[PDB]
Amino acid sequence: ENVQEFVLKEDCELRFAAGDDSDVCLELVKGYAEIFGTELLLNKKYTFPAKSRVAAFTWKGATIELVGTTESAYVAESTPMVIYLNIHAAMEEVRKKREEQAKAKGPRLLLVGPTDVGKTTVSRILCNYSVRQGRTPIFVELDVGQNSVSVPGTVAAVLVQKTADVIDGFERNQPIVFNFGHTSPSANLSLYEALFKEMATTLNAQIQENDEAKIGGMIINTCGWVDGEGYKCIVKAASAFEVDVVIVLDHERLYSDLSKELPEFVRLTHVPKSGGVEQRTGQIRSKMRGENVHRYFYGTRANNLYPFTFDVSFDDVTLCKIGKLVIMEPSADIKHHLFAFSRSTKADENVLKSPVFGFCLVTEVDLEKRTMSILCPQRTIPSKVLVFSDITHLD
Ligand SMILES: Nc1ncnc2c1ncn2[C@@H]1O[C@H](COP(=O)(O)OP(=O)(O)O)[C@@H](O)[C@H]1O
Ligand code: ALF
Ligand SMILES: [Mg+2]
């Protein structure tokens, strides 16, 4: 209940972090402002939980109130927001040109760069800006570590029809989700690459049946792995998704290399990272993976989910594992692991390329009763083919 007031000139952003113990309430009291591309409503109170990192930007100028203990709060005057806006502008230009020559295929954009340069944040701003233009782009999440669509260990895609919630991020409206099963692509690089392609193939077939999605195009977020084998992932992602535009954030050498390698038709743009982007340690990142898993089952402060715990007979499910498909015996070592419900009706070669229904968490294993307790988003298992993930979570 301490109060801070901020006057933001045009093209300025208030960056703040909520206290370690404290909620911070933000209210726009004059003008117009947006948080990572989502417009703030005048006088609406936005409660951010402890440790939240937030940036509120304004094009024309704003006055903003914060109520609560903050670790840091300052106004920055020079951001790359204009750059990020012109990227959206050029995408929409491409949409119109292709519309006037047509079903029109929307432009596809790949965001690349090392850890903590703001690829996710920029993907969010671009998705929001497209929605505010009246478009429905497809957001494609290839980061199996820091995943904003599903649990970690997935490659996923979602049609974006609403701007992100300011506090909770995007609504996960019926995502297409593939179970990769690891927090980094180097754990099985060829499987990771096969999922890209199966994802790209699936999306190409789906947009055939939906013109809005088709002209919406794609914003594709990669992980921060740019060196060695990560570089080749970028080239194969570019190719498999047939991208028109590669945005490289804060990596001149990557940009140089990609310019010499990509098809000449590919427009490549190097842009700086924002001064507000925060370096995150392995610990913080591990904690964020845990909170992602937690959110998948329980939702948010704003939007609670109510997941079911029940027992499942080992005679009613087949547990399997990728690394080719192998059938698993119920064992004590599956405890705390995620399992994906495979859309594939049988435990065969189709599992590898099949998207999934969702996940459960194995909370207990009773070997003698031949049962396991699972946490599950629904009352009854949506599939009897359960695919192992190396991601674990103590609840
Ligand atoms: N302009 C900004 N102001 C404050 N925090 C930011 C800003 N841009 C990014 N961040 C934060 O910095 C962190 C890293 O950004 P992110 O987009 O997740 O990096 P990357 O996706 O490249 O790994 C995130 O916690 C994000 O919320
Ligand atoms: F998307 Al990153 F570090 F590159 F979370
Ligand atoms: Mg990211």
Image (spheres, helix red, strand yellow):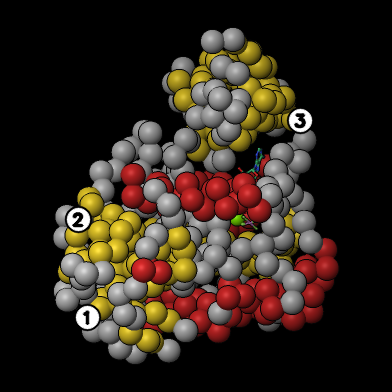
Vertical comparison of 249 with 37: above or below:
below
Q: Is residue 387 left or right of residue 257?
A: left
Which quarter of the rendering shows the N terminus?
top right
User: Mark 1 to mark 3: distance in Å?
Assistant: 55 Å
Horizontal and vertical percent position of residue 375: 28, 54
Three-letter code for the amino acid on which mark 1 is drawn: Thr
Q: Is residue 390 left or right of residue 2?
A: left
Element type at mark 1: loop
Three-letter code for the amino acid on which mark 2 is drawn: Phe
Horizontal and vertical percent position of residue 322: 43, 81
Q: Nearer the viewer, mark 3 or mark 2?
A: 2
Q: Residue at x 45, y 20 (%)?
A: 45
Corner quadrant of residue 321: bottom left
Q: Residues within 10 Å of mark 3 (few under 14, many from 20)?
A: few
Horizontal and vertical percent position of residue 328: 34, 81
The residue tagged 1 is 345
Vertical comparison of 287 with 243: above or below:
above
Whichever of callouts 1 and 3 sits on the residue coming sooner in the sequence is 3
Does residue 99 show up? no
- Residue sitting farthest toward the front: 368
User: Mark 3 to mark 2: distance in Å?
Assistant: 53 Å
Residue 86 vs residue 359, the one in the foreground: 359
Q: Residues within 10 Å of mark 1 (few under 14, many from 20)?
A: few
Q: Quadrant of ligand 2?
A: bottom right
Q: Nearer the viewer, mark 1 or mark 3?
A: 1
Element type at mark 2: strand
- Residue 77's mark? 3
Residue 90 vs residue 345, the one in the foreground: 345
The residue tagged 2 is 310
Residue 269 vs residue 286, the one in the foreground: 286
Does residue 268 show up? yes
